[PDB]
Amino acid sequence: NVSGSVKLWVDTTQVPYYKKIVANFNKKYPDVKVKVTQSPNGSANAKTDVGKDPAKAADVFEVANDQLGSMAEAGYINPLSPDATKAVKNNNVAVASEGVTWKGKMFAYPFAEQAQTIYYNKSKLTADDVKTWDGLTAKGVLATDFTNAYNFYPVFLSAGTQLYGKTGETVKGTDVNSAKGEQAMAWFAQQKSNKGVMQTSNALNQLKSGKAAAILDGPWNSANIKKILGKNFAVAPYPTIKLDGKDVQMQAFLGIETFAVNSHASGSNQKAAATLASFITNKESQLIVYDHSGQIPVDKTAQKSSKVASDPVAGAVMTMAKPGNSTLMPKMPQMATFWNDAAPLINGAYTGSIPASQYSTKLDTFVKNISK
Ligand SMILES: OC[C@H]1O[C@H](O[C@H]2[C@H](O)[C@@H](O)[C@@H](O[C@H]3[C@H](O)[C@@H](O)[C@@H](O)O[C@@H]3CO)O[C@@H]2CO)[C@H](O)[C@@H](O)[C@@H]1O
Ligand SMILES: [Cl-]
Ligand SMILES: [Cl-]
Image (cartoon, rainbow, N blue to C red; front, side, top):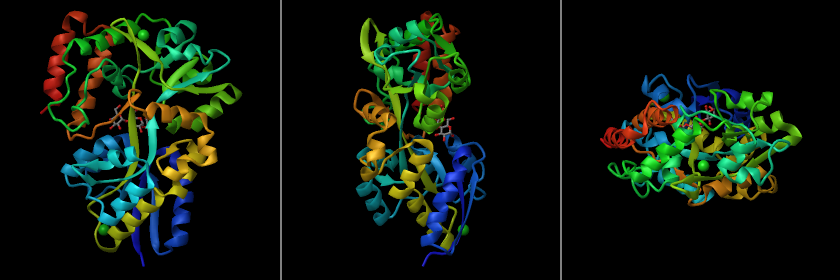
């Protein structure tokens, strides 16, 4: 039997359907008292919401895979048991297991495959228009945010650089302090004068008002964008961009969304938390998340269900996940520093605060900063 009390943290608009998932959980485990709330600052900030006070945080919490190495090294999350590991590995696609594995051990329960795509109004742009960045932006406005390094760091990967080495595990393996890195910096700078590129902190609102024809966004907004655009909804994988005069695919990050178990829980409550984490990331639960938000399951069987297989967003995400189209977010303990330093590097190139004469120096300093 499983008993205990657990607090579950999810993102704000997910609460209603996680209550449904928890109702399903309680059909099987009637003696576990679950309290579902939003987290203080979201899954993108689990690192710091938990780290502020691990013992006060939720017992099960949503967290993106890049945060896992830091949290594992800090002792905030424990390795999954052999049986829990086997279930994750057998039930989900390979990249989901890679996403949660740190130094050979799994530290979270994966449930969604995240890659950004182009979402666009098909009354304003065609499927062919969205194939290239310059062609798209010559025909309509793309609204985006150069202060968000998750949007634009992957241009460095398109340029041929590595982030923490071949598989994201090498402390000194970021080699963006190179001519290839400078090509990406130059691309950011070029976008400031591209009249088809609108800087905004709320790209979704610009799409909704009609001031943008396209945005880059991820599947956490799939159902939201389908509702906004209605019959004008369309989606595509990322386009090509020109780097050093060559057309190359513009990458996104590939992220794996997970739930992790807070290592503070003990006794019954710990067993209840692990049971909940497993359940809310199971196939049925992944499909409920899909039904409500449009996020893409990592479960092998769910990905091949007729409804997922026929969803154009799922198809675009599957394309994005292929080699060359995205890179799995690394999970090095340094990642919080990486993100903090990457955003002003990129935005400085975009705004001109970093001029071309300083690209090499700034990239050298960046690599030193993130490689400790
Ligand atoms: O920008 C730095 C930031 O990048 C990464 O965060 C991204 C998440 O991985 C990704 O899931 C997405 O987050 C959204 C949630 O999924 C959604 O439920 C809701 O909370 O909105 C979030 C977006 O605001 O996008 C973010 C990037 O914006 C990385 O995981 C972070 O650790 C890193 O700090
Ligand atoms: Cl381009
Ligand atoms: Cl406890």
